[PDB]
Image 1 (cartoon, rainbow, N blue to C red):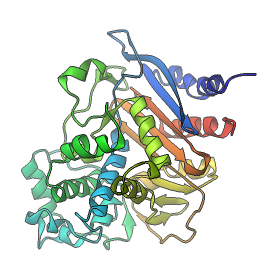
Image 2: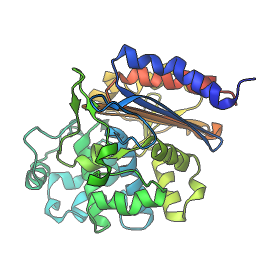
Image 3: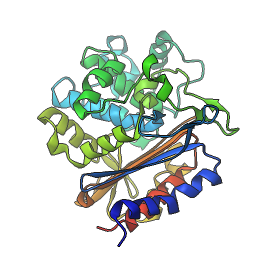
Image 4: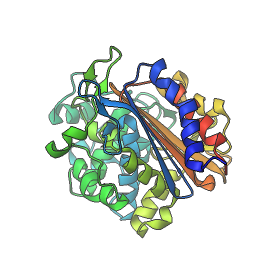
Length: 359
């Protein structure tokens, strides 16, 4: 006797709302999409000092969830014939031809297996010239293709090459090509002056208001800002790729194709992928220190999971994000906060909600 919208709101109140007080989080947006119906739940303030409530217009930083858009851009360029994932970066960034990094192929860059790229660029690598010099001075460590080490410079370089192959800056790849193709009208690499009123403050661990600062190859690694409606639309596209023209449909499918495994995690393009149903521990393991911060041997896919799910966490200094979707259940969920909370809490709360919603 309780309508489905209320049942979903109750589950979000039970599992996500307590996080606001536990982690002193000013604002949160949680969305669920099920069977093409969208449910949006907003809590708290996008700006504490302005007493401005979080709402459907609130723009949040996606952090590493941005890599999903970079992966989609790569799938689009590949399916248009602009790149092959077997190409090396010097084919497009000519200044890298005949350098050691030109031995790594695009898929290895997108999926973090160059064997010598860390989580972040060095602090002093700032300018375009400094980024190029960094890649020219790169030298292999581990055998190329054997070890996964999660890396912003790695997928950032992939993104730059994708942009080169499409003859536009990366920001314009997303804002002029990818976002319009996915029907996202409130998603940005650079938030225009006319929308800054909707851009939430992030909040640091001292609850002080902040927003992301510029950095090297920031756009492809962690550069996107979006709203909850737009992120529900992005989940919708991933749930229904057959609803887009062939090139974008194939681009989306490319991001869903698992490439190798590390234990129970399948590395797709941008997305992490898992057999469904996935135990909670499987999902937590994907965000463990061992997987996120250390190098790990990759193995070929053995079980190609027929029934599967995908997720991705992301953070910036002042924001947290989690997105997850389950194709055969026709369901997905997005969480956006303007303060980081532990990845494990995001995964746990989403797991409880998604498993309890009636089919």
